[PDB]
Image (cartoon, rainbow over the protein chains, first blue to last red):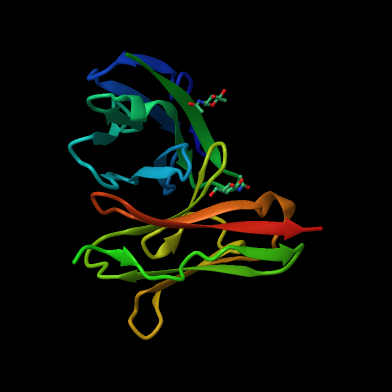
Length: 108
Length: 108
Ligand SMILES: *[C@@H]1O[C@H](CO)[C@@H](O)[C@H](O)[C@H]1NC(C)=O
Ligand SMILES: *[C@@H]1O[C@H](CO)[C@@H](O)[C@H](O)[C@H]1NC(C)=O
């Protein structure tokens, strides 16, 4: 079986300023494939690769390979701000690609 | 010194269908920081992380840490197609971030 993303994954969310929000990507049959979290933006921002956050460890947290099956990948956006509004995706390096996207709406 | 991107890096380019095109990111003072190449799209696509292409090794090639200074990172897009049009960025996990973007125009 190829990797698939179990649903619900990457559910859209809303938040007030300062609230913490999680996006969860649950991957079935990941095997040796890699998971990356990205924010859609111009330019986009890599947020995590495999088991490590790319940068800003106090802003983004990644709990990779958790859950009962070691197959839940939870990205936390801490202290949400207006600049965090937008679309977050988790993507797996399959051919063809496998991905799931959800929106963060920020209320002031 | 923090990482910086030497200019010219990530120069815009044009191509006919089937042509190969390179984007080069030349990083001064990279240290232990990581380089990622991303395509802006909805959703964006991670193309490479550190020294390895994310996926589609026959489509994207990465020559990481080449040049005289071992500080040129060259991403090749092989066999350019209409779907390859858009903005390619290299980004380094500094705080704050360091990045450079160039456009690929595809002619039919
Ligand atoms: C996120 O993507 C949806 C399409 O799935 C789009 O309608 C929405 O505007 C995007 N959110 C942004 C750009 O903040
Ligand atoms: C790439 O980004 C530039 C802004 O720097 C924008 O004008 C252009 O439309 C983009 N190219 C696309 C979306 O193909």
